[PDB]
Amino acid sequence: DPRPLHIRRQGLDPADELLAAGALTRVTAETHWMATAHAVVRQVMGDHQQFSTRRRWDPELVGNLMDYDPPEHTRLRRKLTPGFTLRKMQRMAPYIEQIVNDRLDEMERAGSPADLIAFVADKVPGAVLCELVGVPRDDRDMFMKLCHGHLDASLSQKRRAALGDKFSRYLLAMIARERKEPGEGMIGAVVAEYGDDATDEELRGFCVQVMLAGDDNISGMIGLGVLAMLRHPEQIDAFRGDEQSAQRAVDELIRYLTVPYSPTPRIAREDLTLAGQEIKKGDSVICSLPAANRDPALAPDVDRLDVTREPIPHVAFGHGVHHCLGAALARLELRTVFTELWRRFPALRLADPAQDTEFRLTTPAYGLTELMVAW
Ligand code: HEM
Image 1 (cartoon, rainbow, N blue to C red):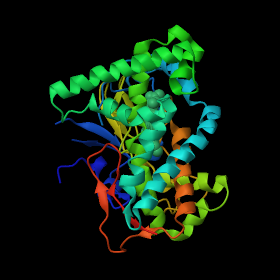
Image 2: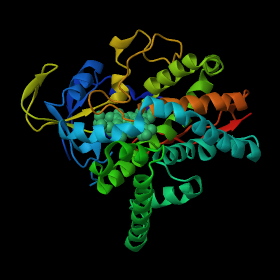
Image 3: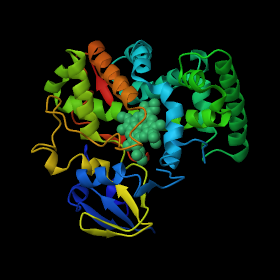
Image 4: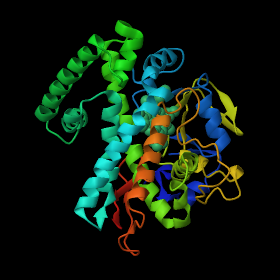
């Protein structure tokens, strides 16, 4: 197998060989350090003074938070933060419920059995991001096409450049409308707070980064999440009670499934000794978030999904100053999807108990390509 250890999974778990990798070891044509222990990953990601983020990494946008470190990163994140406050996330909840129920309506109309990934997992995330950004409902299909299209390598140059011209024109008019009268969306929140200090280029950059950062991780979580819950049916009761129970179940699913294989690679800013290893200035460190969230020190049963467990402080959203800017949105979106899904389809089940599981192996986030369910 040519695939790097950190990208290997076995079912819903990290592959056995990744789970047996030491806390911090060398892996290889580039050679890097691979961190698998929870405390080592926390040390690497939390210490931005010794470990900077590799720039222009792909699992160049202006104001792409992942490219900078404090203080430059701190100023940029500060500027974007207004679009992600907890009070603003609370106000999104009804909109997110409506998006989810509109997709569950299309699935319901198609009839049992149906593919949950095509109807729900692959559609809800981008619609929630459009809602967050401030894109008008009737423009969302077009917006998703323009945004991903201007970055689609499989297209012809002519096609990709035309989509990019349209995307720019669309974004700039949206930005001008928000500056004139700020709305409740992300752009409006940034310009309401910082006005002209937030440049059009920064805003365009913030928009693209967010569209890219909150899509695959969420669709992977919706698909894998439903599959995990169906495999542990008694635990579905956590989505049939109070909000706190549902929130704890979402956090547990996020930890147990850890869809991102790794955060941005980190570069040693100088020589240092970590976990008994000699790290030299310039060395690259890849953090296996899935392995770190299965660290035996975290719990005797860290390898089991248990939505009622004493919560385990996981690294699936990262750690330190770059900790996922959309984490609260993600938790809310996921809780909404699962709560509404089981409210609508109480008898949800795999369409065929013996059906194969179709894993999504081509994306930076683990997930499913299809999931046939009955109800
Ligand atoms: C369950 C889903 C999600 C997971 C597991 C996830 C995971 C992560 C991780 C691991 C990082 C840190 C990367 C690093 O330190 O190198 C990160 C950063 C980030 N995430 Fe997420 N994310 C999710 C959903 C979202 C959503 C929905 C949004 C957008 C609304 C989002 C926006 C971002 C942004 C902008 C950053 C960069 C923050 C910074 O560099 O300061 N994420 N995410």
